[PDB]
Amino acid sequence: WEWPWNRKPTKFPIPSPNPRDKWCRLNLGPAWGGRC
């Protein structure tokens, strides 16, 4: 009860990731549609 753990981080590591992150450039399929 005396150590710096306030306001935890954000913006996970490594830039706009390829892996399942903002992926999809067109209309998907399996469990998608219209949306990303």
Image (cartoon, grey):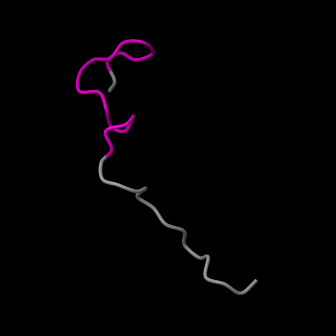
Q: Is residue 5 above or below residue 13?
A: below
Q: Is residue 30 above or below residue 19?
A: above
x and y, in percent, of residue 36 in the image: 32, 27
Residue drawn 54% across and 72% down? 7
Whether residue 6 appears in magenta in the rendering, the answer is: no
Residue drawn 31% across and 39% down? 18
x and y, in percent, of residue 19 in the image: 37, 37
The prevailing secondary structure element of the residues shown in magenta is: loop
The quarter holding residue 25 reads top left
The quarter holding residue 30 reads top left
Residue drawn 40% across and 17% down? 32
Q: Residue furthest left?
A: 25
Q: How many marks?
A: 0
x and y, in percent, of residue 20 in the image: 39, 34
Q: Residue furthest bottom?
A: 2
Which quarter of the figure is the N terminus placed in? bottom right
* Magenta range: 17-34
x and y, in percent, of residue 33 in the image: 35, 15
Instruction: Compare residues 16 and 7 and report the one nearer the observer.
Output: 16
Left or right: where 5 falls relative to 22? right
Residue drawn 43% across and 56% down? 12
The quarter holding residue 24 reads top left
Q: Is residue 3 above or below residue 14?
A: below
Q: Residue furthest top?
A: 29
Whether residue 23 appears in magenta in the rendering, the answer is: yes
Q: Is residue 14 above or below residue 25?
A: below
Instruction: Compare residues 22 and 13 and report the one nearer the observer.
Output: 13
